[PDB]
Image (tube, grey):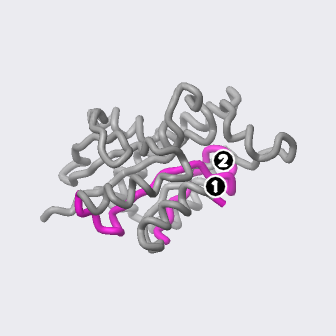
Amino acid sequence: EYTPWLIAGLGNPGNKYYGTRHNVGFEMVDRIAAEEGITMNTNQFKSLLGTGSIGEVPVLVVKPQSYMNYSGEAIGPLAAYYQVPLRHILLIYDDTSLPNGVLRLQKKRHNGLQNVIEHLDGRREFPRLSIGIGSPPGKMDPRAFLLQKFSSEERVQIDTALEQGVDAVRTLVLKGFSGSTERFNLVQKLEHHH
């Protein structure tokens, strides 16, 4: 009966990255931990993590400390250590392919995600929670945009997203969707307009 889940949000550690668009996954993970009362003191495998459960389901919430593109250096070994099956590895990260605040849940672009993919022996069949941050504007390249803080209007949407994502994580893991994740994806898109 031991099948923990690994909830990892991606980002770059440090005051330098605090509040930036690219760190949204870190925000979400700080949110889930908080809500669940899980402290992330533990430092292992290039990451800070905490342990607890969602309902009866045991989980580990993590924030890799190796920097975005090398997230796999943490996740891969971390999963092995705790014996987390691929299907229970939930990655949360910023997605430019979706408008601001639209979440997307999938179970099978972004550098952190390729590296993680790389370390999970290329396997791809794990669930992922994308948090949209929109498209960057084609000047200072699509690079300072990510390293920039969210405008106030964007924050609105973002804060709403953090709240709904927390719920989405709890449903996937414990509750059950009670529709397909694709229906949740549809509702996200619609909500962007309301």
Q: Position of residue 57 (x, y in %)?
A: 22, 54
Closer to the camera in the image, 99 or 82: 82
Q: Position of residue 188 (x, y in %)?
A: 58, 53
Provide the residue span drawn in magenta. 82-109
Which residue is pictured at 51% across the width and 53% down the height?
Answer: 70
Crowd rating for badge 1 (residues with CA inside 10 Å; few <14, some 14–19, many 20+) = some
- Identified by mark 2, the residue type is His
72 with respect to 5 (left or right)? right
- Identified by mark 1, the residue type is Lys
76 with respect to 153 (left or right)? left
- The C terminus sits in image quarter: top right
Q: Is-magenta flag for residue 81? A: no
| For residue 19, above or below residue 58 | above
Residue 184 visible in rendering: no
Task: Specify the farthest residue to the left.
Answer: 1
- The N terminus sits in image quarter: bottom left
Crowd rating for badge 2 (residues with CA inside 10 Å; few <14, some 14–19, many 20+) = few
Task: Specify the farthest residue to the right.
Answer: 139
Helix, strand or loop at disc 1? helix
| For residue 54, above or below residue 182 | above
Q: Is-magenta flag for residue 87? A: yes
Which residue is pictured at 24% across the width and 43% down the height?
Answer: 51
Q: Which mark is residue 189?
A: 1
Residue 148 visible in rendering: yes
Query: Circle 2 is placed at which residue position?
Result: 192
User: Quadrant location of residue 157?
Assistant: top right
Which residue is pictured at 37% across the width and 43% down the height?
Answer: 47
Helix, strand or loop at disc 2? loop
Which residue is pictured at 81% across the width and 45% down the height?
Answer: 141
Closer to the camera in the image, 11 or 103: 11
